[PDB]
Length: 197
Length: 197
Ligand SMILES: CN(C)CC(=O)Nc1ccc2c(c1O)C(=O)C1=C(O)[C@]3(O)C(=O)C(C(N)=O)=C(O)[C@@H](N(C)C)[C@@H]3C[C@@H]1C2
Ligand SMILES: CN(C)CC(=O)Nc1ccc2c(c1O)C(=O)C1=C(O)[C@]3(O)C(=O)C(C(N)=O)=C(O)[C@@H](N(C)C)[C@@H]3C[C@@H]1C2
Ligand SMILES: [Mg+2]
Ligand SMILES: [Mg+2]
Image (cartoon, rainbow over all chains, first blue to last red; front, side, top):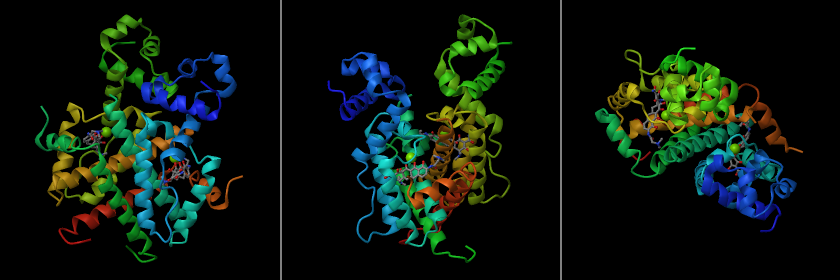
């Protein structure tokens, strides 16, 4: 195929879908593109640079709810942004694993900056707004991971029923439920001000 | 060294600390123990069986707050149990990655069963109690992961300050903060009953 940022990424995405993050090796990428390793090396220097680019690309191509709508509430944003995040993280095999460890990329600077400011101008201190943003991120990541990494791998009464409930759907209900509890818990903090809550 | 469940696990734990979950190969384990691969194979059948055992052992050896104290509140348990969980997950390199994908092991059946019943007899339905337990688990996992996997790998004003705050300590504050918001959010649900909250 052609060898430019976009073509290379597409092949990388398709390859991830087939072999998972572990099967994803520059060697396999070369074959997929129908080229020799030295040709690939000229474009993609290594596995981490390749994965970093993927983490970025996955979000820019599927994470539709990144910036808040006109006059939207901080609660609705956190909910919508979290859902979008989870959605994008699921689009690809090991998607959540690819994202793991990454920090805002330059292209994202704009988007993340805006998220932080939006939270402050709604009553959050940089600290608290950051923490709300973080908790949502950490909660979404772990849920998706435990879901994906689970599928890719004598019981007592309550536990038994628990296990059936956890298979009813692909962890979606439990997530949305936890998401609400998280957002609400943030409310009780914002409105609590300096009072003992 | 000796080759029995405990000696093999110890070597596996020490090895994980040195090479990470990826460097952890049955081949490297054999050398560490000072034995030949076929000797190891007689004991440890494969990487997954080895990792599963580790996930179990890490918790049984460091997760001290697994069952609730006499007459303890569901909020204090969720908080203490979550802290212990995070603590154990940090004790070893890639600890959170080892745990990923695992389900309660037979030895744990007792412990998990008890956690579920304790939540129900405090007003939670199996469903809701499960979800509270899950959200805590998913939140703790993701925080630890993003922390560990981060270390093992032109900025705008707000984002810049945000990044400094996220390095102040090893993600502990942000976690405890999110933990409280999560627990509180669960309260608002329990006491809300059938009323529109
Ligand atoms: C502890 N260590 C990871 C260092 C550290 O905390 N730095 C960080 C400091 C600040 C951030 C960080 C990290 O890692 C992110 O990774 C964010 C996202 O991925 C994003 O989803 C993020 O990048 C985007 C996005 N591009 O749209 C989001 O939608 C945010 N929501 C909450 C899902 C989220 C914003 C985070 C900002
Ligand atoms: C979606 N998929 C993973 C399937 C599924 O959800 N099954 C599951 C169904 C039910 C559970 C599950 C999974 O995976 C656990 O993994 C739990 C723990 O690891 C534990 O930390 C857990 O094993 C222990 C423990 N042994 O002490 C804990 O302390 C619990 N707290 C909340 C940290 C937690 C209980 C979970 C029960
Ligand atoms: Mg991230
Ligand atoms: Mg688990």
